[PDB]
Image (cartoon, rainbow over all chains, first blue to last red; front, side, top):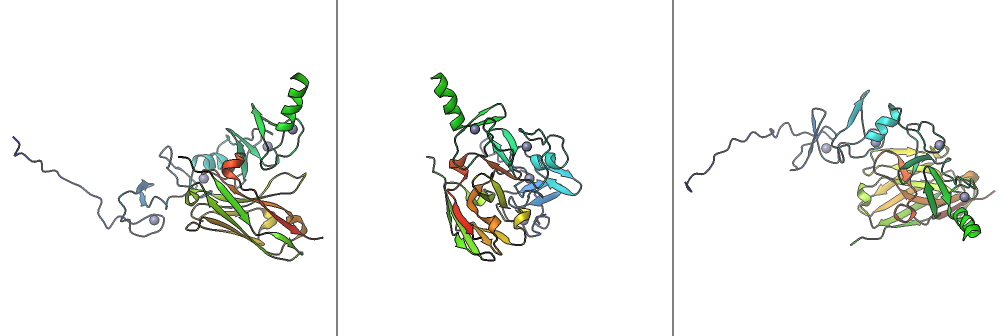
Length: 146
Length: 127
Ligand SMILES: [Zn+2]
Ligand SMILES: [Zn+2]
Ligand SMILES: [Zn+2]
Ligand SMILES: [Zn+2]
């Protein structure tokens, strides 16, 4: 029958409950987040260390010792998996690092594997394994060989 | 369809010890409002030295020990500008100061110069 029209039951989140866990204000937005038994504005759920939006990729956060953390910060604080690609030593929390491609380095470790010079802004380089090689070492290799 | 990333550092110059400078960086070509920003300096011979970090909404802010209590980072997302207030300047602060775009997750820089780094502005504190 074309005359048949459905009557659906709707169970909404009550407007009183929609207070953000990060700013304590009402959420009147259509799109928002649920996490750790709270509701949040998309810009109100941040990493306690770095302050990035927490579930943007992978839809998960990492909670330990009263800290909501992103994957990398969680592993920097608690995980054994935060070693540098050059010196093979653990990356301290609150430490700024340099990532070339998929490998991570200390800034003092961010130097050429051959001539040992510290890289400057705009320096061309090549990454072989976990070794970064400067352009003038690539040119000096190919000069002897052709 | 891809816009070119641009970071233009302003301010800086020559001043005496105890002097003060205000650095600015105008940004375009990426969503600045969703990007953690940095100031990173460099002298010749010496490697790159990170100075200060600021999260997209300014909720997280960090400084190098050498600059704590002297330098102040800030941003204005509506104007796409990053700032650095440099006070109580000393000879060790002499370097080229770059505005560096950070990776979105967990205090990281990247060596993609074209997409994440400016051309820098020179700061010099006399002998
Ligand atoms: Zn909120
Ligand atoms: Zn290292
Ligand atoms: Zn080299
Ligand atoms: Zn984080």
